[PDB]
Image (cartoon, rainbow, N blue to C red; front, side, top):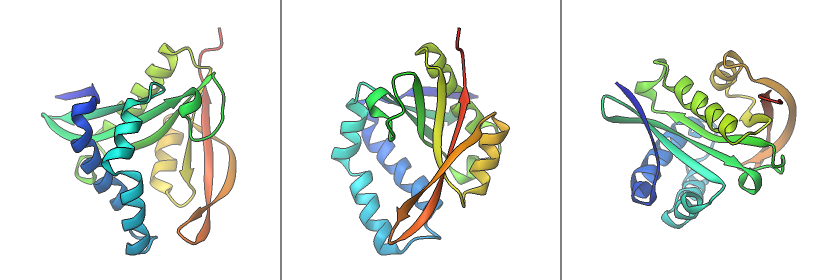
Length: 173
């Protein structure tokens, strides 16, 4: 069966390994091994993730299928967001499903959980940033109701790439 669990301090090691594997398998083709090694060490080292897990405005959730870890999602609100969007929004900063577990509705589960958290936190809108080249993720988000509201350049390695800003308005009552 499918189940999700909020990550705690004891999930640090598991979160770190899952983060590295899924991220590597997502940007591995368009980046040098040297740049990937450096980023993986600066983004997923024990101390960095420990800080993020302890951030009051951040929340991580694991998703499981048959008791096996299949992926995770990281959401931010207020000052924890990677962009200063305000106190009325929630960001899906990271969302990853292990390759072998993709195409089974698990990504949808994680995203809807992010939506549920946003609704519960009374946030007016939910948003995310996604590399323009990630066609699979863009198509998934559009199916989930997200729309591109903007786009800006960002540096990947030593070259600029395009980040698409996608969002959806929630409850306004």
